[PDB]
Image (tube, rainbow, N blue to C red; front, side, top):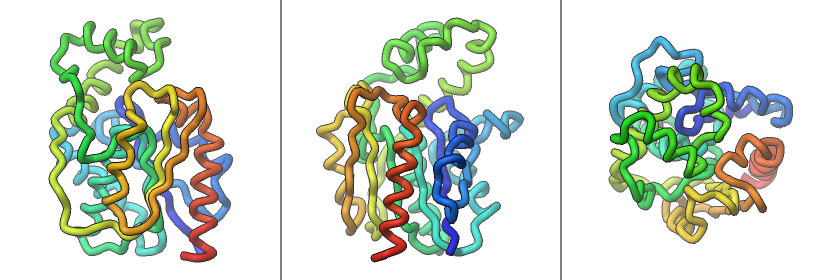
Length: 239
C-alpha cells in the first residue's frame, strides 16, 4: 500500500525544510509537506491570526492530497503543536485515525507554555533573544537583508505558540506517538515529555539525540527519517 506523511515546519520555517526528506524516506511513503500561510510557496497568503485559524488553514492544505488511505503527521516545535491540534481537527471532520504521529522538539501540549512572552518585544530585541535561545540559527544576523523580510514571519509563529491555550479533547488518540528530542535543546524540557503519554492509548516512544540542539531535525534529518521509516515499517507488520 501507500502512506502519506504530512510534515509541518517549526517557527519561521517553510515546507522546504522537508524537501530533502525524499532522499531517505521509504519508497512507499509519499512526502506531503504542508505549507503554513505567509511563507515559502504561500508567501502571498496573509499570516495566520490564531492557532485555530492556522489549523483550519492547514486542513485545507491536507485535503488537497488526502483521499482516505494511511497517513502519519510529523511536526517540529510549533509544527508539533499544530500537528496535535490538526489531527484532532481531522478527526472532528470524520476522517480515520493516523497510523502514527511524530512530535519533534515539542513539549507536551498541556505544558506547551512560554516561560516568556517574546512576541511583543521590538523586532530587534526579539531576534536577539531567539538567537540567544537557539530558536533560529545564529547566522541569521549575517545578512540584514534576510532579517528584514524574515523577522515578521518568525515573530508571527512565536505569537501563535505563545497565545496558545490548551483545551482538552473529546477523544484519546489510538495510534503510537514518537517523540524526538535533542539532549542539548534549551527550549524543550526532557523531564516534561512524560506528559505526552495520556494523549494516546498506544505506546509513546522517546528518542534522544546526543549532543543535539533544537535544530537536530535538520542536522540529523537522516536519522530522524531513519526512525520514521522504522516506525512505519513496524506498523506494516503488526499494526
